[PDB]
Amino acid sequence: TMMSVLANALRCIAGAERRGKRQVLIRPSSKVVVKFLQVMQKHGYIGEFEIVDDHRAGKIVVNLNGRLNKCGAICPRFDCTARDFEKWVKNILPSRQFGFVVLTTSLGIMDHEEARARNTGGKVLGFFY
Amino acid sequence: GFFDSDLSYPTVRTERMKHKRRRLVQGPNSYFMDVKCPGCKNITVVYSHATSEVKCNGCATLLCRPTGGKAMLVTGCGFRKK
Amino acid sequence: VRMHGNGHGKAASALPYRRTPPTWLKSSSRDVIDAVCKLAKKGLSPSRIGMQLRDSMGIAQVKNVTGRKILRILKHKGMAPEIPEDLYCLIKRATQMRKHLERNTKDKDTKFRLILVESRIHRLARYYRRVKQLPPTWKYE
Amino acid sequence: GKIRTKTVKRASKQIVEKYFSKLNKDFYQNKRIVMDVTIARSKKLKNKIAGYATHIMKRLARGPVRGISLKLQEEERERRMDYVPEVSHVDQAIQDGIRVDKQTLAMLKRMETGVPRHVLPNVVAA
Amino acid sequence: TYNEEGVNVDLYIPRKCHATNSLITSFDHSAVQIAIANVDPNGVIDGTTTTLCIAGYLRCQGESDHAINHLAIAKGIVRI
Amino acid sequence: TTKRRNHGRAKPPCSRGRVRPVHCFNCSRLVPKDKSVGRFVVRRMLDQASARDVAEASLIYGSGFPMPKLYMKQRYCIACAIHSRTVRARPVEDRKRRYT
Amino acid sequence: AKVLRMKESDVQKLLAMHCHLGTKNSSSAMKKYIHGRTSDGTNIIDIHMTWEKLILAARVIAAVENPQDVTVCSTRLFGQRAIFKFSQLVGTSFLGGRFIPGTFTNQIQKKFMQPRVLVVTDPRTDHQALREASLVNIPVIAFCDTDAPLEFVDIAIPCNNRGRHSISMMYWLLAREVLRLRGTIPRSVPWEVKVDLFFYRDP
Amino acid sequence: EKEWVPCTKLGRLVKDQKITSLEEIFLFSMPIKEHQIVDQLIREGDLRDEMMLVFPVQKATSAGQRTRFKAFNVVGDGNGHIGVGARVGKEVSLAIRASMIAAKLSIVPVRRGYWGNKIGEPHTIPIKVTGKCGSVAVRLIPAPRGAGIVAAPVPKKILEFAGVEDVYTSSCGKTRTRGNFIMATFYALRKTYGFLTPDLWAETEVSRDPTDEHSEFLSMGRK
RNA sequence: CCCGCGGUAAUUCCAGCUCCAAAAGCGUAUAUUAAUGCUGUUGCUGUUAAAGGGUUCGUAGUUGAACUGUGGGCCACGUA
RNA sequence: CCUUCCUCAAUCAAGAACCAAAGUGUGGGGAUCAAAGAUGAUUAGAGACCAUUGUAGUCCACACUGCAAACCAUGACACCC
RNA sequence: CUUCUUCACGCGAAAGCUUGGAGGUUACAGUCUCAGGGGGGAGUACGUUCGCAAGAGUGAAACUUAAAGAAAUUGACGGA
């Protein structure tokens, strides 16, 4: 099938923005996804979400507004350390100044700009702008 | 379209329509019922989906048939629900 | 996509979302044991018991009614089945199918159907061994 | 092609259009008319106009022929708009408290704060 | 927007799609600006309009009515 | 360049992998049933007065057919169609949309 | 008002003109503002909305500095008189029948006007105009029936428009309120004007 | 006319010295048609009004390679707005001139940017965005105050006429196909107001018809 | 170079003159580097322009979901 | 279907198992349609179209084969519109 | 299985493109895989391996050349 639901979720999410599906109940979360969702939410892109139970992997109800321009996942994940921060960002943000790149860290799942600010490398997840 | 509502909450239309494993959460669609054989003053727990049989044990015989969907109750067997 | 079929078999029973059975009546582990055994002594395959039970006993979801799944109980309770039953079900056909095939002339279907199953038979067994409950050094033939 | 050219038709028309009514159905005076109410060029063209003017009138004479008029009818219609007191197509209506649909009565009821009515659809029927 | 010193810098602080709020560009010819005149008791007071400029797309989508209809729900006019 | 999608065959979506070829009764190279148009019709007999002659001489009654009539199961394809001023490029879109 | 909820008389009017039962027994439920598959090619169209829309129509109508620059349209025979009757009264700019474009697609044809707005009534028939609205950032309110497409009419007036008084009544009725606002017509007016002259064609 | 009546009311209002700025169109959501409106509105000296492309157009036709000229005018002024023209004519100049009007007409607001972050003022694209066309691909990328910039000569002239200096380029495609190239460019230029900014945006407060703000005035000296 | 000049009133040939370009360097060759995301991790392609097999199984190969990772509490105040 | 069972999978070189026509061997098989051929006719030529037949084939038993504009010229699997 | 109304932007050079199209991608990135990579020479060669046998499988360089292609468009034309 496909594995990274997070990833399915991004393409799909994107579409959701794009034609304006303003809430989704996604099927069916892990620990991971959420941390990431939160970041965007922290960053004024979508509204807020709410995690639904299931007895098997959760569903989450997601608030959006119209602020996302693009959200990616990178398969594969990749190390991050110094310069590579420059390159990724340059690669994917319409200008270096807005958007976030997210990698997965020791310090938690985290954006690169902040990461740049935290001064820790780790592995790369994706990005949103 | 998708405004007034909630996907999260359905309402008065809106449960009836969702299908089985896309009921927001699936849930045993079938259910159980209580059935009585006029055969005796004693009665039986039943599946509304059964694939096999009920025997009355007020007299060993079967009140329903396996058939795919809801199983076929028959014979003046009376049932109520949970 | 479906592993012998272009179309889709959704089918399904929908699990008791409620794990707290059942909005009308509790039973004891003793009961369930009692039942099980009685049935198991009655000889269904456990899965088959389960099915059977589901209507026949008209008491549901084995995993709930004592916080288990039949097979382990049975196992522990010395009423394990001989084998990995799905592999069996497939086998019993397969066997049958070889027999049929033996009768037959030309039937490509029995070949096709046999293939898939036997393979499957392999997968599963390879799997049982993978889960160390194939008997080691084991195969179907 | 005894098609009255565009120019023609336009002209024969136009002369009644600017020079309302009068005429004949006779070509002959309508002819003279053609001479007289225009300052046209060739005779043929006037006559042809005329022939049609006779013509157009001849069927105007029996109607407001496709696309054509004299403006009175209009001022009758205008004066016929006026059916008001000779019609109340309103309260001809046979019931103030009404024989009608349930919910519609119901939205109305909640809207009409608990007011007491029988709530019944138009039938039940599709 | 704001420049290195802060400060708006550069022309035309854009429009935005007063429903979806998607940006409004400069070549939207199905976008519209409704200033909708407020009622008072018996009337309307005007000067007071609820005003929107809304993009084209929705007009394509049946949500020119509809979406605005929700939007308008979110801004109620004559309601129950 | 390509001119008509299904290219006659009415089976791509469905299930009819390959389907019934026929000699087309008018030319007779062998062809599949859905690349030939069909309009299996009954068919009329006699002119008016030859019928009148036959009508007076109609010592013939009812049975579900009060004087009977023919029936031609007609199936045309390129081969014969053509000459018979039968089937060709209409205007565009009708090359995709069915009779009423 | 305060209060803007329908009266039994209003109700009387509405059902009377016969605007309220749908087209085809089901219809485009993209316009799912019905609730009720109703016999013989209709539905119930839920009125409530209709109303809510209508008054809104006014709330925006009442903005226009130049009410003439509120542009009315009607290809249905059953609408012209009416549109005028609204127009005469409002000063609208009206559009009967076959539109013929270049109108604001051309500013160089005589036609040229440049209102804020256009109100359409047979979306369907009235496509050029829609198209025109679509050219020029114009919205279009509209008398819509239940399968009357609504694309690029913004603000639907759920509306059975089967001729007679249906259309006209609706239009007239509509008017009454706008008039209450801009215009000063008080409510327990008659509102003088009648569908009888809103009406249509004769004889 | 040289005394072009700006028969639009806008062009009127405009000619009539109320609201002479593009932005007022863009802002107010306005569209145009009348070419003089801009030409009126902004015309201060040199603006950077230009002809660019000069093409022959043919319809082959029996007794005729029916030949016509297509010509491209780019109109711009050195910060924020560009105005595009391609037009065809049976005379070359006429095509230019036809293109001129289109050029006037096809004016767009340019949200410029910088790169890295703001400096005293933008001079870049504010984003990295793309124009695609038949066989064309450019994506125009943020650079800073001293760039010679990747890619094509061809738009570059325009860019200059619209007011930016430094942006990165990645050009991909059939440069081969220059007509389209410009079309792509324009398009690109059009997305010079694309992307939901996090960078001003906030809320756009209403701004009511500056046209219909003078409705009566527009209905005066005018019906 | 390649597009092409040239059968005479040739724009590219012949000479002249004039001009031009770069320049004390410049022609040339061959190769090689980019242009080429025109081999592509970034970044190609494969319905009609090259390209997805007639069909399936299938070890190799790759790829492979969730879940028990988590912080918490309290206080202070300021504080939107 | 409230059955059991806990990732069981996915897709996949090699590698296997299939592949219409037709052919191909070993046997049916006989009727027809008809490759081969034969006849006409035609043509400028024409052993080609066209005709009139007619031999192999055809169906089949039985083998074997691998080639078929073997076309949803559109790998699969995925999740959406 | 649709057809397919009809709609979707979208995607596309178009032609055209649904179930969950050739859509949701140079704002280039779910997996796995096959293939493809000017044209011609040749899919051929005693090249080589299956295969009874066809021939399949596998598979070139030399030599050659500036195009070849594609869709649309208009035109022209037709023993249409």
Image: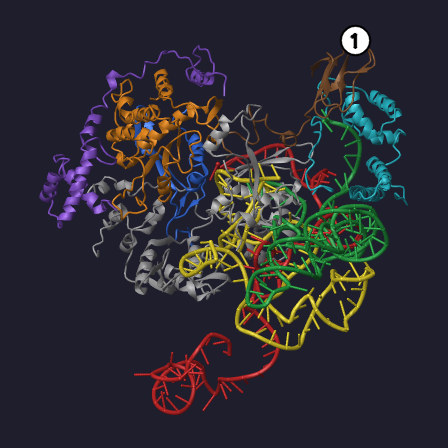
Chain colours: B brown, C cyan, D purple, E blue, G orange, I red, J green, K yellow
Q: Badge 1 local density, few (<14 within 10 Å), some, or many (20+)? A: few
Query: Tag 1's secondary structure?
Result: loop
Subunit of label 1: B
* Rendered-image quadrant of the C terminus of chain G: top left
Q: Amino acid at mark 1?
A: Cys
Residue G93 image position (x, y, % from top left):
27, 36
Residue D122 image position (x, y, % from top left):
46, 17
Residue I25 image position (x, y, % from top left):
49, 85
Q: Nearer the viewer, residue J19 or E21?
A: J19
Residue A128 falls left or right of residue J38: left
Please tell me whether residue B14 is drawn above or below residue G109 in the rendered image: above
Q: Nearer the viewer, residue H67 or B14?
A: H67
Figure disc tally: 1
Residue H185 quadrant: bottom left
Q: Nearer the viewer, residue D110 or K79?
A: K79
* Rendered-image quadrant of the N terminus of chain G: top left
Is residue G200 at all visible to an observer of this figure? yes
Residue under the point 87% across and 22% down: C38
Which residue carries the number 1 mark?
B40
Residue under the point 83% across and 29% down: C46
Q: Nearer the viewer, residue C55 or H200?
A: C55
Please tell me whether residue A125 is drawn above or below residue G4 in the rendered image: below
Is residue A103 at all visible to an observer of this figure? no
Residue J7 quadrant: top right
Residue J6 image position (x, y, % from top left):
79, 38
Please tell me whether residue H96 is drawn above or below residue C71 in the rendered image: below
Q: Residue furthest top?
A: B41
Residue G150 quadrant: top left
